[PDB]
Image 1 (cartoon, rainbow, N blue to C red):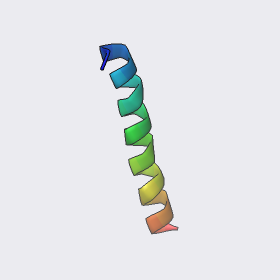
Image 2: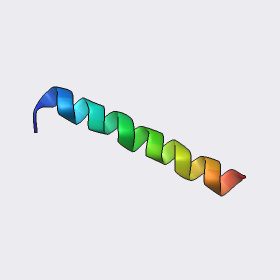
Image 3: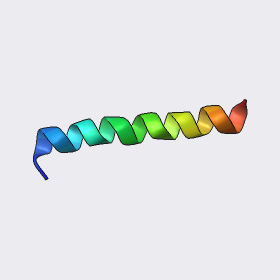
Length: 26
């Protein structure tokens, strides 16, 4: 995978982890 696309996908994966925590903790 092209690196800049990969970095954008890593942004999404990290924000998804944050969404998981927010839901766990609400």
